[PDB]
Amino acid sequence: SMNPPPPETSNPNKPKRQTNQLQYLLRVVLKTLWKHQFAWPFQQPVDAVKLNLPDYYKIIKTPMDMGTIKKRLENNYYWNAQECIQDFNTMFTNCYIYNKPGDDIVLMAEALEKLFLQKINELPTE
Ligand SMILES: Cc1nnn(C2CCNCC2)c1-c1cccc(Oc2cc(Br)ccc2Br)n1
Ligand SMILES: [Cl-]
Ligand SMILES: [Cl-]
Image (cartoon, rainbow, N blue to C red; front, side, top):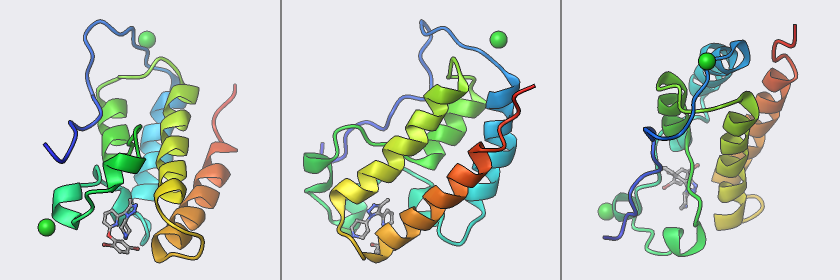
Protein backbone atom coordinates (compact mmCIF):
# COMPACT_ATOMS: atom_id res chain seq x y z
CA SER A 1 0.00 0.00 0.00
CA MET A 2 1.03 3.63 -0.24
CA ASN A 3 0.22 4.34 3.37
CA PRO A 4 2.17 2.17 5.79
CA PRO A 5 0.20 0.79 8.72
CA PRO A 6 -0.14 3.47 11.38
CA PRO A 7 2.07 3.22 14.47
CA GLU A 8 0.76 0.68 16.91
CA THR A 9 -1.32 1.84 19.85
CA SER A 10 -1.52 -1.62 21.50
CA ASN A 11 1.12 -4.30 22.01
CA PRO A 12 0.02 -7.12 24.32
CA ASN A 13 3.50 -8.34 25.25
CA LYS A 14 4.94 -4.88 26.04
CA PRO A 15 5.09 -4.04 29.76
CA LYS A 16 3.05 -0.98 30.71
CA ARG A 17 2.70 1.54 33.52
CA GLN A 18 0.27 4.17 34.73
CA THR A 19 2.09 7.00 36.48
CA ASN A 20 1.21 10.50 37.62
CA GLN A 21 3.49 11.97 34.97
CA LEU A 22 1.87 9.93 32.20
CA GLN A 23 -1.57 10.96 33.46
CA TYR A 24 -0.45 14.62 33.33
CA LEU A 25 0.91 14.13 29.81
CA LEU A 26 -2.59 13.09 28.74
CA ARG A 27 -4.82 15.38 30.81
CA VAL A 28 -2.73 18.52 30.58
CA VAL A 29 -0.04 18.35 27.91
CA LEU A 30 -1.74 16.45 25.07
CA LYS A 31 -5.26 17.73 25.67
CA THR A 32 -4.10 21.37 25.80
CA LEU A 33 -1.88 21.16 22.72
CA TRP A 34 -4.74 19.37 20.94
CA LYS A 35 -6.90 22.53 21.19
CA HIS A 36 -4.27 24.89 19.78
CA GLN A 37 -5.11 26.50 16.44
CA PHE A 38 -2.02 24.83 14.92
CA ALA A 39 -2.73 21.31 16.20
CA TRP A 40 -4.93 20.02 13.39
CA PRO A 41 -2.20 18.79 10.94
CA PHE A 42 -0.74 16.75 13.83
CA GLN A 43 -3.96 15.14 15.11
CA GLN A 44 -3.75 12.03 12.91
CA PRO A 45 -1.18 10.05 10.93
CA VAL A 46 -0.10 11.67 7.68
CA ASP A 47 -2.30 10.13 4.99
CA ALA A 48 -0.06 10.18 1.94
CA VAL A 49 -2.87 9.03 -0.36
CA LYS A 50 -5.22 11.79 0.78
CA LEU A 51 -2.51 14.47 0.72
CA ASN A 52 -0.95 13.32 -2.58
CA LEU A 53 2.48 12.87 -0.94
CA PRO A 54 4.05 9.69 -2.40
CA ASP A 55 7.41 10.91 -1.07
CA TYR A 56 6.32 11.38 2.58
CA TYR A 57 7.05 7.79 3.69
CA LYS A 58 10.05 7.65 1.36
CA ILE A 59 11.55 10.24 3.74
CA ILE A 60 9.83 9.61 7.09
CA LYS A 61 10.57 6.14 8.47
CA THR A 62 9.41 6.67 12.08
CA PRO A 63 6.07 8.45 11.68
CA MET A 64 4.33 9.87 14.72
CA ASP A 65 1.34 12.12 15.43
CA MET A 66 -0.74 13.31 18.38
CA GLY A 67 -3.68 11.04 17.54
CA THR A 68 -1.38 8.05 18.01
CA ILE A 69 0.08 9.59 21.16
CA LYS A 70 -3.42 10.26 22.56
CA LYS A 71 -4.46 6.65 21.93
CA ARG A 72 -1.20 5.32 23.39
CA LEU A 73 -1.80 7.34 26.56
CA GLU A 74 -5.45 6.26 26.75
CA ASN A 75 -4.42 2.63 26.26
CA ASN A 76 -1.58 2.79 28.83
CA TYR A 77 0.91 1.89 26.12
CA TYR A 78 3.93 3.56 27.69
CA TRP A 79 6.34 2.56 30.45
CA ASN A 80 7.33 6.11 31.40
CA ALA A 81 6.89 9.77 30.59
CA GLN A 82 10.18 10.00 28.67
CA GLU A 83 8.90 7.38 26.22
CA CYS A 84 5.86 9.58 25.47
CA ILE A 85 7.99 12.73 25.29
CA GLN A 86 10.14 10.94 22.70
CA ASP A 87 7.05 10.43 20.53
CA PHE A 88 6.32 14.17 20.61
CA ASN A 89 9.95 14.84 19.69
CA THR A 90 9.75 12.40 16.78
CA MET A 91 6.57 14.09 15.54
CA PHE A 92 8.18 17.56 15.53
CA THR A 93 11.46 16.41 14.01
CA ASN A 94 9.63 14.51 11.25
CA CYS A 95 7.97 17.77 10.26
CA TYR A 96 11.33 19.52 10.01
CA ILE A 97 12.88 16.61 8.09
CA TYR A 98 10.10 16.43 5.48
CA ASN A 99 9.57 20.19 5.01
CA LYS A 100 11.70 23.35 4.77
CA PRO A 101 12.58 26.29 7.01
CA GLY A 102 9.85 28.92 6.77
CA ASP A 103 7.10 26.60 5.50
CA ASP A 104 3.69 27.19 7.11
CA ILE A 105 3.70 23.67 8.58
CA VAL A 106 7.16 24.28 10.08
CA LEU A 107 6.02 27.57 11.65
CA MET A 108 3.19 25.59 13.20
CA ALA A 109 5.48 22.84 14.51
CA GLU A 110 7.91 25.43 15.91
CA ALA A 111 5.14 27.13 17.88
CA LEU A 112 3.72 23.83 19.14
CA GLU A 113 7.17 22.60 20.17
CA LYS A 114 7.75 25.72 22.27
CA LEU A 115 4.36 25.26 23.97
CA PHE A 116 5.11 21.56 24.52
CA LEU A 117 8.45 22.41 26.16
CA GLN A 118 6.76 24.98 28.38
CA LYS A 119 4.23 22.38 29.51
CA ILE A 120 6.80 19.64 30.18
CA ASN A 121 8.82 22.00 32.38
CA GLU A 122 5.74 21.69 34.67
CA LEU A 123 5.64 17.90 34.82
CA PRO A 124 4.86 16.86 38.42
CA THR A 125 8.03 15.72 40.18
CA GLU A 126 6.88 15.20 43.78
C1 LIG B 1 2.11 16.90 9.75
C2 LIG B 1 2.51 17.40 8.38
N1 LIG B 1 3.79 17.54 8.00
N2 LIG B 1 3.84 18.01 6.79
N3 LIG B 1 2.61 18.20 6.36
C3 LIG B 1 2.34 18.71 4.99
C4 LIG B 1 2.38 20.19 4.92
C5 LIG B 1 2.08 20.67 3.49
N4 LIG B 1 3.03 20.05 2.54
C6 LIG B 1 3.02 18.57 2.60
C7 LIG B 1 3.32 18.09 4.02
C8 LIG B 1 1.71 17.85 7.29
C9 LIG B 1 0.21 17.91 7.17
C10 LIG B 1 -0.58 16.90 7.74
C11 LIG B 1 -1.96 16.97 7.62
C12 LIG B 1 -2.49 18.03 6.92
C13 LIG B 1 -1.62 18.97 6.40
O1 LIG B 1 -2.21 20.00 5.72
C14 LIG B 1 -1.46 21.13 5.45
C15 LIG B 1 -1.08 21.97 6.46
C16 LIG B 1 -0.38 23.11 6.14
BR1 LIG B 1 0.12 24.31 7.52
C17 LIG B 1 -0.07 23.45 4.84
C18 LIG B 1 -0.46 22.62 3.82
C19 LIG B 1 -1.16 21.46 4.14
BR2 LIG B 1 -1.75 20.29 2.76
N5 LIG B 1 -0.32 18.92 6.51
CL1 LIG C 1 1.40 0.73 36.73
CL1 LIG D 1 -5.92 12.56 -2.78
